[PDB]
Length: 257
Ligand SMILES: [Cu+2]
Image (cartoon, rainbow, N blue to C red; front, side):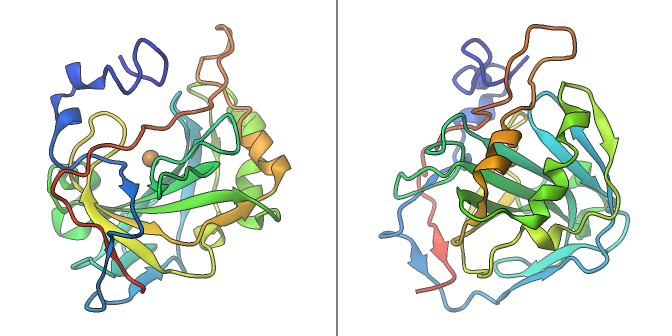
């Protein structure tokens, strides 16, 4: 199996999933001084108006909000993308200390957490088929930094008690993901992979420059989930992040100067 522990952590993943040592693995450190600004990139289009959330679940790796992706309700397009990408899931990578938690780093700096809004290319029929394509997924990464409480996240915060342990799930309809975005849509983009097994290199990464803020109380609560199942020794779901991987010969582009 796999996890974030000493014996099944990121350093062990390559034995079950050889692609862990591939050419386009994620996350990566974003060196703001070498990223290439590209004014040819069309603007990032986020259309979450009729988004329809379904459930929130603790799969032992993170909390996950699942959406109905049977139609073009909550979609992502524009930016470096060709076609339409449907939102299917949102989860969070969180640290144990405010100075760590994010998967992507900026000039080596790590944020307290990182939200990943996963979308898949509609020209592929469904998510399962999409992950098998180099351009099958588009994942929006949003950093979290301590500040004023974030209303959009309080919705999640308010339900955490119900999904404390691995396998627990709860109804999570009428959740508006628009509430998870910072003011600016400026971003960095590069070709990468899923950051948890199977680690398929099928995603176009779009990492927002502006982190959203969350209150200390909110962050504390997001660290109260468990990796373990109910009844087993309690293992706090903290530091469920994969460290930065070798960029190799990939170019990180910026949508802003
Ligand atoms: Cu993720």
